[PDB]
Amino acid sequence: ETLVRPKPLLLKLLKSVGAQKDTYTMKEVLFYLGQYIMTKRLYDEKQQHIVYCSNDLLGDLFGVPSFSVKEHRKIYTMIYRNLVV
Amino acid sequence: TSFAEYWKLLSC
């Protein structure tokens, strides 16, 4: 059901917090990614849709110091740039 | 609103 292939920085990200494989569903990459953040306490404690990726792997792949979960389209766009679909 | 839910809004 089209499985996707993370590119090397996102696969590294995914592996770091458990993941075992090279190919995934979108669901799966989204659960592992959400896991990575919450796990890396990259989220802002008072307005927790904000995420910081300065001096982190996450900014290496997204190219920005921070971002807002609300920005659904912008965030999907960045994830896809990191997948062969 | 939790990060959890905002991200659960992002998927869904």
Image (cartoon, coloured by chain):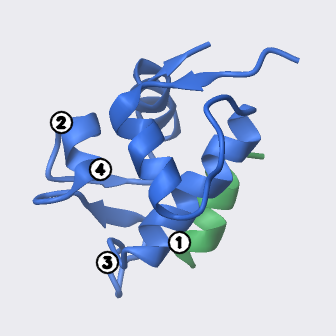
* Amino acid, disc 3: Asp
Q: Are marks 2 and 4 on the same chain?
A: yes
Q: Are marks 1 and 4 in contact (CB under 8 Å)?
A: no
Secondary element at image label 3: loop
Q: Which residue is mark 4?
A: A58
Q: Report x, y in % for residue A73.
A: 50, 30
At label 4, counting other C-alpha atoms closer than 10 Å, the crowd grade (few under 14, some 14-19, many 20 or more) is many
Specify the label residue B3 is tagged with.
1
Secondary element at image label 2: loop
Q: Which residue is painted at 36% across and 54% down in the image?
A: A68
Q: Report x, y in % for residue A37.
A: 43, 66
* Amino acid, disc 4: Leu
N-terminal-most mark, 4 or 3 = 3
Chain ID, mark 2: A
Q: Marks 2/4: CA distance?
A: 8 Å
Closest to the camera, between mark 2 and mark 1, is 2
Of all chains in the rendering, the one displayed in blue is: A
Q: Are marks 2 and 4 in contact (CB under 8 Å)?
A: no
Q: Which residue is mark 3?
A: A44
Foreground residue, A13 or A68? A13
Q: Colour of chain B?
A: green
Residue A32 visible in this rendered orientation of the protein: yes
Q: Which residue is painted at 61% across and 32% down in the image?
A: A22
Q: Marks 1/3: CA distance?
A: 9 Å
N-terminal-most mark, 2 or 3 = 3
* Amino acid, disc 1: Phe
Specify the label residue A63 is tagged with.
2
- The picture quadrant where one finds residue A49 is bottom left
Q: Report x, y in % for residue A28.
A: 72, 45
